Length: 50
Image (cartoon, helix red, strand yellow):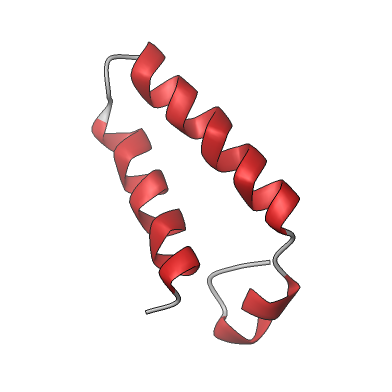
């Protein structure tokens, strides 16, 4: 549950951690495409909140 600020409290850390791992593995495997970097950068902003 993320992008709308009010739903950040509903984020499941198991789901978030798993998808970050999957995306980071795919990022390395596909020789670091900008598309995947951008998704990972947005996820890192949620974890930081601001």
